[PDB]
Figure 1 (cartoon, rainbow, N blue to C red):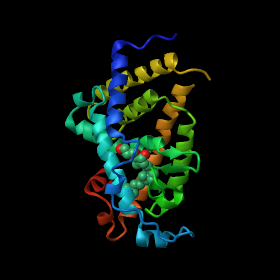
Figure 2: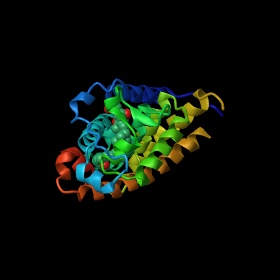
Figure 3: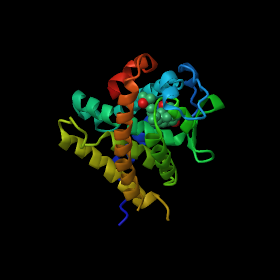
Figure 4: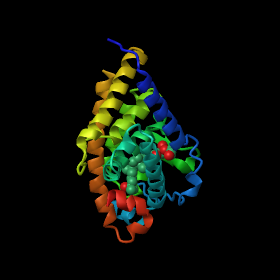
Length: 250
Ligand SMILES: C=C1/C(=C\C=C2/CCC[C@]3(C)[C@@H]([C@H](C)CCCC(C)(C)O)CC[C@@H]23)C[C@@H](O)[C@@H](OCCCO)[C@@H]1O
């Protein structure tokens, strides 16, 4: 059966597309405002050297902090999110921020050279730039794999914005109080996505592939948390981060 999208489901999709267009600048025009990227000579991928310099960390921490602000704005526009308590809104935002950043970065990700290309060569991020921010291959290589797997799903922007909304409104996040209300909001979004795929997505399992990405994101989130903890032990690291980043990942 291929039921048509209800008027409500159509409205949810319109709101989410509008929220994404207002919070995701595909020209990356604010990037000149971040602390500049610095690429030290590290052809050897030396952990000692990367931690000593953390040359890409101020730029990527500013990029991520800016992105977290955009994700907060997006989340606030998800139909039903404002019905949650302020406490549950913050729990969901803090636990999903890194996953939504990984999802939304797929728009700048390119399979041409396996990089996140945000305009000119200065704002092109490769595996080597992430190692220069203090992260290791145990996070970066599965993250690149995830990006390619997501790129190959060829999501319609409707499916992309619904996936990010479903990711944020997850009832199984530690510390959530009203799990039943969060689950009702998520089911409303999941049914919208399932209905959209069934009547708008041409041929040639897409919903199950999208739900598998959400599970992959949990593993990536856990690895990022372990790595962030290591990064945080580096003396003077806090100055290379931002107050928002420190709070979200602390
Ligand atoms: C962020 C965005 C972009 C890329 C994301 C990347 C590439 C560099 C390395 C990142 C930032 C990974 C790092 C492992 C995270 C490390 C973080 C610390 C704190 C250092 O532990 C996770 C996501 C990866 C660019 C652009 O798509 C932004 O979208 C355009 C902007 C519209 O708002 C988006 O949001």
